[PDB]
Image (tube, rainbow, N blue to C red):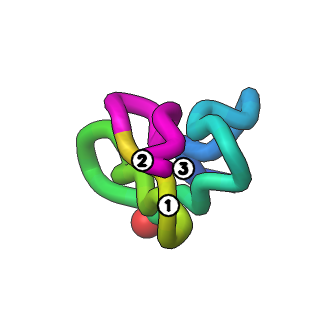
Amino acid sequence: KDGDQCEGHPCLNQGHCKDGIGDYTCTCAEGFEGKNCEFSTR
Ligand SMILES: [O-]
């Protein structure tokens, strides 16, 4: 276990989360955005 940076469910609204050497990145599902994939555009 080295670095999944996805510990502690960080993204919101079923936002997926990849990995990186400095903070992961959030991927909002179609219809969400915001710093956390928080916001439902609709
Ligand atoms: O990653």
Q: Residue at x 32, y 56 (%)?
A: 20
Q: Residue under circle 1?
A: 31
Indicate if the residue with disc 1 has its beta carbon within 8 Å of ligand 1: no
Residue tagged by mark 3?
3
Residue at mark 2: C-beta within 8 A of ligand 1: no
- Quarter of the image with the N terminus in it: bottom right
Q: On the rendered structure, is 12 left or right of 41? A: right
The amino acid type found where label 1 is placed reads Gly
Q: Which residue is mark 2?
A: 41
Picture quadrant where residue 6 is located: top right
- Could you say which is closer to the camera, residue 29 or residue 3? 29
Q: Amino acid at mark 3?
A: Gly
Sequence-wise first label, 3 or 1: 3
- Judge the density around disc 1: few (<14), some (14-19), many (≥20) Cα neighbours within 10 Å: few
Which secondary structure, mark 3? loop
20 versus 35 height, above or below: below
Range drawn in magenta? 34-42
Residue 28 position within the rendered picture, expressed as x and y whole percent measured from the top left: 47, 58
Residues at circles 3 and 1 in contact by the CB criterion of under 8 Å: no
